[PDB]
Amino acid sequence: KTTLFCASDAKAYEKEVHNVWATHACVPTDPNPQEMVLANVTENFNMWKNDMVEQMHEDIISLWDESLKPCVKLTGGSAITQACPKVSFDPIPLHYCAPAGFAILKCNNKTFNGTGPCRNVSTVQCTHGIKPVVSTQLLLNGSLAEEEIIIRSENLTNNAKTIIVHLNESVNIVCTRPNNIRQAHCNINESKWNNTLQKVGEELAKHFPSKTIKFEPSSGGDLEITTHSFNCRGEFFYCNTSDLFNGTYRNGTYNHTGRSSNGTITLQCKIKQIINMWQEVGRAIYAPPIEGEITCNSNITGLLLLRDDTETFRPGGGDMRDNWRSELYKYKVVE
Amino acid sequence: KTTLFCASDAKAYEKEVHNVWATHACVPTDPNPQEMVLANVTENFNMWKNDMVEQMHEDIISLWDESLKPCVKLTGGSAITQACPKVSFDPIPLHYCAPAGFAILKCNNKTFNGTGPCRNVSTVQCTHGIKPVVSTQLLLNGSLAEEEIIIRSENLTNNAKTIIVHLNESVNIVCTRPNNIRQAHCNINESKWNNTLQKVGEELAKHFPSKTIKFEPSSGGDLEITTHSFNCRGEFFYCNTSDLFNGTYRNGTYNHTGRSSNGTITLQCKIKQIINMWQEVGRAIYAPPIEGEITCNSNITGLLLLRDDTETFRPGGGDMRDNWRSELYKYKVVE
Amino acid sequence: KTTLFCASDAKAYEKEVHNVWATHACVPTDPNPQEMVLANVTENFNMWKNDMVEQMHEDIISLWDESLKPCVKLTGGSAITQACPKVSFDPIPLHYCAPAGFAILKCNNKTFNGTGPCRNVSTVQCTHGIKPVVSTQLLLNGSLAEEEIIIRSENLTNNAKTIIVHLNESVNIVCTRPNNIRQAHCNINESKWNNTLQKVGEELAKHFPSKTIKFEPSSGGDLEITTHSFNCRGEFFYCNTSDLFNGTYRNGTYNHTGRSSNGTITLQCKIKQIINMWQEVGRAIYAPPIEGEITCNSNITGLLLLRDDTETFRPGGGDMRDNWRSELYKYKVVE
Amino acid sequence: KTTLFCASDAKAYEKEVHNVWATHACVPTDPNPQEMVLANVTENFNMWKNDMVEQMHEDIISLWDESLKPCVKLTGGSAITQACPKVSFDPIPLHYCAPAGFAILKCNNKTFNGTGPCRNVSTVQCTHGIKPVVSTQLLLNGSLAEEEIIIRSENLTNNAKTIIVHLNESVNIVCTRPNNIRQAHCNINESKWNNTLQKVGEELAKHFPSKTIKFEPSSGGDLEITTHSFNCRGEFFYCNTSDLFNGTYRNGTYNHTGRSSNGTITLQCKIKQIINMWQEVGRAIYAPPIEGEITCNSNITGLLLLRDDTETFRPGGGDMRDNWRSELYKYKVVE
Ligand SMILES: CNCc1ccc2c(c1)[C@@H](CC[C@H](O)CO)[C@H](CNC(=N)N)[C@H]2NC(=O)C(=O)Nc1ccc(Cl)c(F)c1
Ligand SMILES: CNCc1ccc2c(c1)[C@@H](CC[C@H](O)CO)[C@H](CNC(=N)N)[C@H]2NC(=O)C(=O)Nc1ccc(Cl)c(F)c1
Ligand SMILES: CNCc1ccc2c(c1)[C@@H](CC[C@H](O)CO)[C@H](CNC(=N)N)[C@H]2NC(=O)C(=O)Nc1ccc(Cl)c(F)c1
Ligand SMILES: CNCc1ccc2c(c1)[C@@H](CC[C@H](O)CO)[C@H](CNC(=N)N)[C@H]2NC(=O)C(=O)Nc1ccc(Cl)c(F)c1
Ligand SMILES: *[C@@H]1O[C@H](CO)[C@@H](O)[C@H](O)[C@H]1NC(C)=O
Ligand SMILES: *[C@@H]1O[C@H](CO)[C@@H](O)[C@H](O)[C@H]1NC(C)=O
Ligand SMILES: *[C@@H]1O[C@H](CO)[C@@H](O)[C@H](O)[C@H]1NC(C)=O
Ligand SMILES: *[C@@H]1O[C@H](CO)[C@@H](O)[C@H](O)[C@H]1NC(C)=O
Ligand SMILES: *[C@@H]1O[C@H](CO)[C@@H](O)[C@H](O)[C@H]1NC(C)=O
Ligand SMILES: *[C@@H]1O[C@H](CO)[C@@H](O)[C@H](O)[C@H]1NC(C)=O
Ligand SMILES: *[C@@H]1O[C@H](CO)[C@@H](O)[C@H](O)[C@H]1NC(C)=O
Ligand SMILES: *[C@@H]1O[C@H](CO)[C@@H](O)[C@H](O)[C@H]1NC(C)=O
Ligand SMILES: *[C@@H]1O[C@H](CO)[C@@H](O)[C@H](O)[C@H]1NC(C)=O
Ligand SMILES: *[C@@H]1O[C@H](CO)[C@@H](O)[C@H](O)[C@H]1NC(C)=O
Ligand SMILES: *[C@@H]1O[C@H](CO)[C@@H](O)[C@H](O)[C@H]1NC(C)=O
Ligand SMILES: *[C@@H]1O[C@H](CO)[C@@H](O)[C@H](O)[C@H]1NC(C)=O
Ligand SMILES: *[C@@H]1O[C@H](CO)[C@@H](O)[C@H](O)[C@H]1NC(C)=O
Ligand SMILES: *[C@@H]1O[C@H](CO)[C@@H](O)[C@H](O)[C@H]1NC(C)=O
Ligand SMILES: *[C@@H]1O[C@H](CO)[C@@H](O)[C@H](O)[C@H]1NC(C)=O
Ligand SMILES: *[C@@H]1O[C@H](CO)[C@@H](O)[C@H](O)[C@H]1NC(C)=O
Ligand SMILES: *[C@@H]1O[C@H](CO)[C@@H](O)[C@H](O)[C@H]1NC(C)=O
Ligand SMILES: *[C@@H]1O[C@H](CO)[C@@H](O)[C@H](O)[C@H]1NC(C)=O
Ligand SMILES: *[C@@H]1O[C@H](CO)[C@@H](O)[C@H](O)[C@H]1NC(C)=O
Ligand SMILES: *[C@@H]1O[C@H](CO)[C@@H](O)[C@H](O)[C@H]1NC(C)=O
């Protein structure tokens, strides 16, 4: 254990809130990246017991509390008011770094599921650039897997633990509230979603080799988890995924049961002002949306699922630590 | 430097907030105190750089935070609203104690002014019972000097430094909002205040030997310090002292120039709901006062003064550290 | 996170080194403990991330450095020598206690594994009496589980994580060197060992589907961990467990295949002077053993195991922090 | 509050013990000296409450414990023996450095007494090169004030607080045991000492504006502080200063009353093997001196004085943190 520090390519002249946070919170990044390969050493990792995740989680909570200040923050019977201006919000990469006396070991196995022994490992000073993208159900703007799709989970047997599906080919998603000021929509290409959900069904079938693999929507919870919720240019998008997690993989082949038009799935979305926070147990009230075309052009790079004759997988999330684990699985800080 | 702990006679059954906080934060007072005298040993004390004061200060800050919750708390544009019930509020004595391996040296030189060598020292484990009374200008319900009045200051030649006047006999002040509901008043017996300012002028004259001494009201600043402000029964009293600090000591003889009637000085008071906090920079808003007759009967045991041919002294205070120093002056925690 | 203090009933007249250390380092035990029970609760515990264990670890390191002074201590090629008298050495219980305002919550579910939620928790200010017994492989003189033998592990699937087996009924082990001066031996009743190993195999079989469950001696490494090593009356015993951790649990029955005679397993032991320290990475050299009959009559109360068709368990140990966790599986410092 | 790191031009091939400690304890100094000057800015410093002093203190304690091992070390009833080889001993400069996310502000006021506000401040990453020279009474081989001679004290009215006299012109002292094997002597040119003490009396008279300034020898105590004690090439010199601190500054002129011969003051020295340690309380016993001619040619750069019709000043010291303060007064560590 230690206390890592962050490095970023943030610019002090920029008024984007990730930049403004990182300029006072993190140190300039290193153009001199030294990495030492060692093929004979083998080390053990547990991405689900990684304290880098806790440190980044606290850092990102700080980022949001200093950047996305709500008009009202309701917590523990208390109500906190403050100025809630519209801001320029677009996440930037953050590197996490070990101080003197410590190193970060990085697993070089491209098929590593994030748990157990990795026997090609290198030593580095900082992780790669990580954008702190808060979202659920879908992981956006992450890093793709270099080889095959990877299924990660602390206990695939345990239906309560979140499953992280690490994709190897990105799936583009475009969400837009165009120029009702709270109604929006996302567009996704049905063909790419079809083939990536087919190969995800294959990878999931290998861990469930008399079991049909079904994809169905979230059954219940707060709207933040029953929809694809995320933040776009400052506004809180809640996008219905009934037509996205909706299909069946049986006998090696995927059939999509959700609904398209001219080859595209469109999710209906609402820009909400009352938010159930992820940083703590409480609610946050923001100002109505800004004017004009609000669009985010993101890459789906991962999935957050929960498992329930056959096995059924629904979208999940909510604990943004899982978001940070999707990217910090390779890393472990050693002395 | 060590972490001290508190000890009190707080009762588990008492709804009064000091008792409630002490049942959870302090231990019961040792009914078998031990004190060992060292009459040949001489040790150096400095009441103005005493870590015991910082410790008691933080203890009382959290006492007030857990007990006297305001309806609104405003810190530079940010407003926290909570439940603000009326509570029962009567300060109880607190003893401060060193853990194992540490002791508390107590200077028993009844002449001691707070700084320098003390030659009659002793060793205890805990201080005497100290009521944490939050006040300006007047020190209430403290413990009196044994022989003559003591004048304490970090640096008498520095007019910015607060002077603490430690009285050897107490002046009774009775303060009441009787049964506009925010109007109250305070009665002081003018002959006792006469004699007290007489001999305080004597003792200050010794330190400024012509220089006719002059007592005058506070020059300016926030209402909390320009008045005798205190808390009685939970309500915040602000009482004008322009008739109380109003005199001239000249040619060894005292001269009170404030208005009086039937031998008693009466201070006009307001119960205010908007407060400038002492714990931190900010404002605190409380509920309208409770119904009925609100009375506190206190012993003025000390004065807080500021010095501006002739020397003029005006009531001061504000930094509650000085309130604690008025009682922690004769102690020092040694390993 | 806080600084706890120890309590003991050490007596100042005792020449025994645990007493000598505790009288100077701990406070007399308080004789009316109020276990404030509660019953709508669950709080999460993690015996494998517990600051209590580290503070106890540091205090025991200090005790051993002040009490069991080696003739030589070699640390990083640096050799410091000092007086190495033979001392009276018999561990005494130490209660650990939270200071003023902080509490120790305690889980009373007597099937509680050590990590996860707990449901019948009380509150005290001090733990029970814990004797700091330093040993490997077998835990001695601990507290027994009341109901059933419990298996504790940071992660039962990571073979590299130490497994603690909290036993139920103590197995008496008697270790002696009689009146070669460094040759000793220890007797264990083989029937009770067979019984206990059957129960341990039963519960490890419910934790591991149902492969045959073999017990084998320690792989390799320093003698301190390859043997049951402990300290008795100051002398360092290294006892061979090859005829002890040696059986096969198959068919729901346990078959012991270590050598016995007349119904007793006897381990062969050497008393050593050169010791690989547990407090630090270094070596200590002690004096030749004392004259006379050196024997300890101890209760095996727990086991320290390591896992590698079938699963094999071997005696582990080495990190005395796990010895502390076995009696602080816990409790918890709370405010 | 942070943990600094050192930086030295030490050589990994020099057997000199400061070099050998600094190659395994320090990083290389960098020709990266980016000084940042900020005149608008102005900050508060207190050279007497500066954690850099304590961090350098512990570092130098570590160096001495690893470099000048005594044959015998007596502390608290315990006696520790180790090899005590004669080593090559010559202190080298050490830079102290704030890690990433921290900076070191340095006050560029050349008249700064070390306490209060400084209007010209600059930020760098590391202090200037500071030789950790352990001595009493006279500060050796340090940095010189750039304009006037500076008087430093956390309280000049408290006679117990050490006074540091920062000289602007260095006074040469040559100490030698030539080729009784423990008899040595120091030569100091009497006229430069005459001028140095006259201007020191001038500054002290400014701060004591009557008060004939009188330099007298140290009253009493351990030999370490009643003499100018220091270490030269590994040997512990104790040199008598009764002919050094022995003069009177009256009506603006200084008269040296110390015994002089041929215009040079000669201090008699003993090389001692039993030393009262400065690191902790206890004694340390070293081997007899080496053979040959043992000489240090040093620059007196400051004084350590203590104040008793007049004011008397005697040489003092013995808390090597004051030695560190004489160089670490300019600096303060910031986030
Ligand atoms: C089986 N799953 C367990 C599960 C389920 C739901 C939730 C958690 C855990 C919490 C995580 C706690 C964290 O670990 C503490 O640090 C969190 C509690 N907080 C409440 N108010 N309920 C709650 N998640 C959120 O509400 C959340 O993600 N909202 C949100 C906002 C903005 C955006 Cl853009 C967004 F995409 C999402
Ligand atoms: C020359 N004098 C310096 C001086 C002057 C005024 C004041 C200080 C210092 C502060 C002390 C800071 C402390 O040291 C930090 O811990 C404090 C700042 N805080 C603000 N909001 N301005 C401010 N004092 C108060 O406002 C205060 O006493 N109010 C108060 C309330 C209730 C009761 Cl019953 C009462 F009797 C008093
Ligand atoms: C897979 N297991 C990991 C493993 C393995 C072996 C060992 C550790 C860890 C260390 C623990 C370090 C500690 O955590 C730091 O505080 C310790 C290192 N130290 C060295 N010299 N090698 C080393 N254990 C010991 O050597 C030890 O127990 N000896 C000992 C003496 C007297 C008695 Cl009576 C006794 F019963 C035992
Ligand atoms: C009014 N003055 C207070 C005063 C007075 C004398 C002394 C202190 C304080 C201690 C400082 C404690 C430190 O702060 C803890 O870290 C120290 C205690 N230690 C003992 N054994 N008495 C003791 N000083 C020394 O003995 C010392 O300097 N010897 C020494 C050796 C080698 C060399 Cl070359 C040298 F030039 C000097
Ligand atoms: C991940 O791989 C390890 C082996 O390296 C295995 O023990 C574990 O069960 C795997 N987990 C999943 C979810 O595949
Ligand atoms: C991604 O992984 C799948 C297997 O899950 C594989 O079939 C596909 O070819 C991969 N895509 C690549 C390597 O571009
Ligand atoms: C550690 O890895 C195991 C598998 O090796 C995994 O099941 C578990 O979720 C991980 N985290 C733990 C046990 O805290
Ligand atoms: C996962 O959970 C199952 C049952 O919930 C359990 O048998 C297994 O030991 C757990 N851990 C793993 C598979 O690492
Ligand atoms: C998603 O849409 C379907 C149909 O439009 C609806 O039945 C479902 O309740 C919606 N879910 C959410 C979370 O709005
Ligand atoms: C899949 O989508 C269709 C409409 O597109 C909907 O009727 C159906 O219920 C969905 N499947 C679910 C919710 O399991
Ligand atoms: C993903 O990245 C692109 C380009 O940086 C950006 O336009 C988009 O808004 C991002 N999506 C999210 C959710 O931040
Ligand atoms: C307090 O006593 C000390 C000790 O002599 C003295 O130096 C100081 O001036 C005194 N201060 C006051 C305010 O009396
Ligand atoms: C209080 O002190 C004054 C001197 O300041 C003295 O004249 C007076 O008699 C004292 N009163 C007592 C001791 O009651
Ligand atoms: C210094 O000591 C004097 C008397 O001992 C005291 O009045 C003063 O407050 C102390 N501190 C200073 C001058 O900063
Ligand atoms: C006290 O004040 C005087 C002038 O106001 C000043 O000379 C002195 O340095 C101050 N501090 C002390 C005496 O500690
Ligand atoms: C106190 O009252 C007088 C007259 O009654 C007034 O001049 C003065 O301003 C008042 N001071 C405060 C602080 O209210
Ligand atoms: C003293 O009190 C009178 C009222 O009785 C007032 O007029 C006078 O201004 C006061 N003295 C001051 C404020 O200095
Ligand atoms: C002082 O003490 C009396 C009696 O204990 C009490 O009535 C009064 O309210 C106290 N004053 C303050 C300011 O607490
Ligand atoms: C140092 O200068 C400050 C003014 O910045 C002054 O307050 C302090 O008394 C001075 N101290 C000494 C020892 O000269
Ligand atoms: C050193 O300072 C003294 C006064 O303290 C001054 O008279 C002398 O000229 C200075 N020497 C220099 C600046 O070289
Ligand atoms: C200083 O020393 C010289 C001899 O080197 C002597 O002649 C001179 O008078 C002395 N001056 C003073 C002021 O003591
Ligand atoms: C220094 O020398 C003088 C006379 O030479 C002597 O009286 C004094 O005691 C010596 N000081 C010490 C500390 O030995
Ligand atoms: C100064 O030196 C002379 C001769 O060395 C000595 O007699 C005198 O006592 C000294 N002054 C002191 C010790 O104050
Ligand atoms: C002072 O520096 C010189 C030159 O490096 C050196 O010879 C001498 O030993 C140093 N003095 C001390 C006391 O270390």
Image (spheres, coloured by chain):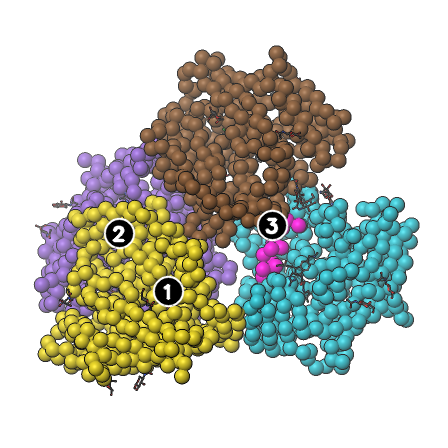
Chain colours: A cyan, B yellow, C brown, D purple
- In the rendering, which numbered label is found on residue C42? 3
Mark 2 to mark 1: distance in Å? 29 Å
The answer to whether tags 2 and 3 share a subunit is no
Q: Is mark 1 within 8 Å of ligand 18?
A: yes
- Name the main secondary structure of what is drawn in magenta: helix
Query: Mark 1 is on which residue type?
Result: Asp
Do the numbered discs 2 and 1 sit on residues whose CB atoms are within 8 Å?
Answer: no
Query: Mark 3 is on which residue type?
Result: Thr
Where A216 falls versus D76 (above or below)? below
- In the rendering, which numbered label is found on residue B105? 2
Q: Quadrant of ligand 7?
A: top right
Q: Residues within 10 Å of mark 3 (few under 14, many from 20)?
A: few
Residue at position x 59%, y 51% in the image: C40
Q: Residues within 10 Å of mark 1 (few under 14, many from 20)?
A: some
The answer to which of marks 2 and 1 sits earlier in the sequence is 1
- In the rendering, which numbered label is found on residue B90? 1
Residue at position x 37%, y 73% in the image: B294
Circle 3 chain: C
Asked which secondary structure carries label 1, the reply is loop
Circle 2 chain: B
Q: Nearer the viewer, residue A258 or B264?
A: B264
Residue A30: horizontal and vertical position, in percent?
59, 60
Residue D10 shown left or right of residue A251 in the figure: left
Query: Mark 2 is on which residue type?
Result: Leu
Residue at position x 53%, y 29% in the image: C140
Asked which secondary structure carries label 2, the reply is strand
Residue at position x 65%, y 26% in the image: C197
Q: Quadrant of residue D67?
A: top left
